[PDB]
Amino acid sequence: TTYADFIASGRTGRRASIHD
Amino acid sequence: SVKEFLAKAKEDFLKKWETPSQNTAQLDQFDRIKTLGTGSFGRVMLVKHKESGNHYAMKILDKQKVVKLKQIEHTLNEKRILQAVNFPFLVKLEFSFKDNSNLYMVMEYVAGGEMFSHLRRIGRFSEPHARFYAAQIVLTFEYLHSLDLIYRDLKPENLLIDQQGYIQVTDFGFAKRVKGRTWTLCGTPEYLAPEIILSKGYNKAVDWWALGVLIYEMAAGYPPFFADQPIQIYEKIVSGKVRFPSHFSSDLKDLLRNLLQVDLTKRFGNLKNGVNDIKNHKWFATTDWIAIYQRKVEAPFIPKFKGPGDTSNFDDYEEEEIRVSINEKCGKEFTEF
Ligand SMILES: Nc1ncnc2c1ncn2[C@@H]1O[C@H](COP(=O)(O)OP(=O)(O)NP(=O)(O)O)[C@@H](O)[C@H]1O
Ligand SMILES: [Ca+2]
Ligand SMILES: [Ca+2]
């Protein structure tokens, strides 16, 4: 499932902002 | 009415924008208790103000690091804007000041923790629950955009839940005052509008895109565009193809197709009716916008609070002692702070 794939992924924790 | 409200709000903002407050407190007025969050230039700590005993969130930034990373403008923007705005769902800056080494921004402590933790904990929010928070963001961007402000970092990690279950928007690090187009590549990969990624130059509409991402994430439990790496994410974003969970209502899907719209002549928030396109959408039909603004609606979730200074709604971070040099650093760069 989409959820299972998200939850197994590397970006489920707090996400950092990015800039230039 | 809203017209009237917005024009007075703009007078109020412009006064403070034109003559920002400076140096209203000093470091030794506060006892530092615990880190609530960190970042590139420093950290955010729970602190207690000695003379009042009130708790605050103190954002601490290393001046030298800010200059090195070329983030002076963004940092000056953050403080200058945060000190001039006033709106029920924006966190309040209570004090600001600087010392030889650091910049300090002291805000009202919002104890409910990040929307992020509650969202991942519960998995996903019901549409009424998601809709209650989304309305807050809609009103907030209507306010901000009317002052020529773009927020540019909408995400659950930057939204705090207060003691009444209402949203407090924090982190004005990429907030900017601008009429027309701007070009900085900034935000959070999952939430970037296609026009940011394609380096076309962009405007306030990117905030409305980000809202669609946020409503999706709240309602689905996962973002509309995800992958293991940023690059992959940008591919899906520019692809623009979105799929919706089976449980999304027809109204929700229709609203999101209008927000997550690659075509700026068609994205909601960006048309002739402006925000009203959003406020009058079917998905928001049960929403009492005034009551929301007034905070008279019962919140779906009320954080547990084990008294003042409680940080159980925050993750733990490793601590480190705050250094202040006996040498002034970067004085000229931060004169206006
Ligand atoms: N007013 C506040 N009340 C309670 N907690 C807060 C407050 N402001 C910030 N925090 C916490 O501190 C974290 C970092 O604050 P933030 O303003 O986002 O700093 P940052 O240096 O820009 N780090 P980053 O997340 O990479 O942008 C937030 O996500 C919250 O968990
Ligand atoms: Ca942040
Ligand atoms: Ca930030």
Image: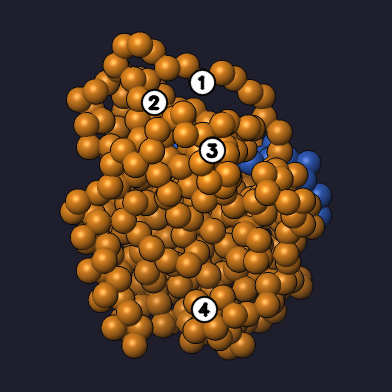
Chain colours: A blue, B orange
Residue sitting nearer the eye, B236 or B18: B18
Question: Contact (CB < 8 A) between labels 2 and 1?
Answer: yes
Q: Which residue is mark 1?
A: B322
- Residue holding disc 4: B294
| N-terminal label among 3 and 1 | 3
Q: For the residue labelled by badge 4, is the local secondary structure a helix, a strand or a loop?
A: helix
| Residue to which mark 2 is pinned | B102
Chain for mark 1?
B
* Structural distance between the alpha carbons of marks 4 and 3: 32 Å
Please tell me which residue is depicted at 30% across the width and 71% down the height of the picture. Answer: B9
Task: Answer with left or right where residue B213 lies relative to residue B309.
Answer: left
Q: Residues within 10 Å of mark 1 (few under 14, many from 20)?
A: few
Disc 3 vs disc 1: Cβ atoms closer than 8 Å?
no
Q: Nearer the viewer, mark 2 or mark 3?
A: 3
Q: Residue at x 43, y 49 (%)?
A: B94
Residue indicated by mark 3: B50
Amino acid found under the numbered disc labelled 2:
Asn
Q: Quadrant of the N terminus of chain B?
A: bottom left
Q: Could you say whether the residue bearing mark 3 is in a helix, strand or loop?
A: loop
Q: State yes or no: Cβ of the residue under disc 1 lies below 8 Å from any atom of ligand 1.
A: no
Q: CA distance from mark 4 to mark 2?
A: 37 Å
